[PDB]
Length: 47
Length: 63
Image (cartoon, rainbow over all chains, first blue to last red; front, side, top):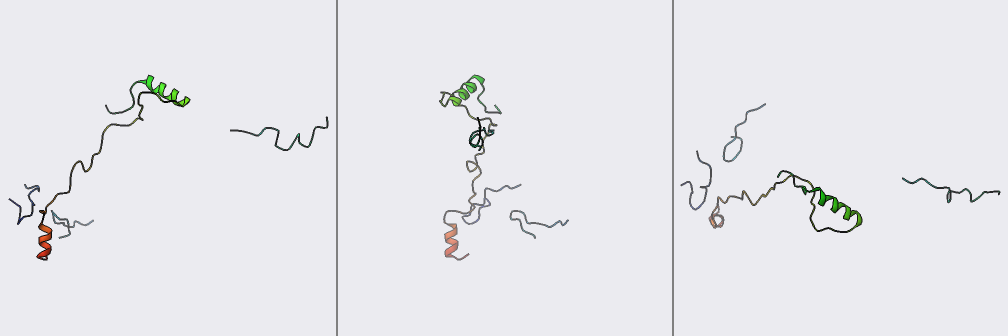
């Protein structure tokens, strides 16, 4: 019906500023250290 | 039907115990979420207002 010259345009529904736009194509119209290895009792203990 | 968690607590508990050990279990335990899909392109497709050879013919006729 609406198809024009081999083009299948059929599958279409047919029934501030106020600009006007064209329809169908819109455009303007833990762990804490332990004592060892912490450097005491490694220089100490006079007993 | 809204949520998708495994509905039985026993299988979840067994799953997490075996996971703590390091072993697997038989059943599947997926994470919680809502159900539903979004299958786009298994859906609205590109309309073809043109025919098969409309564009090439327009090219030859230069329009």
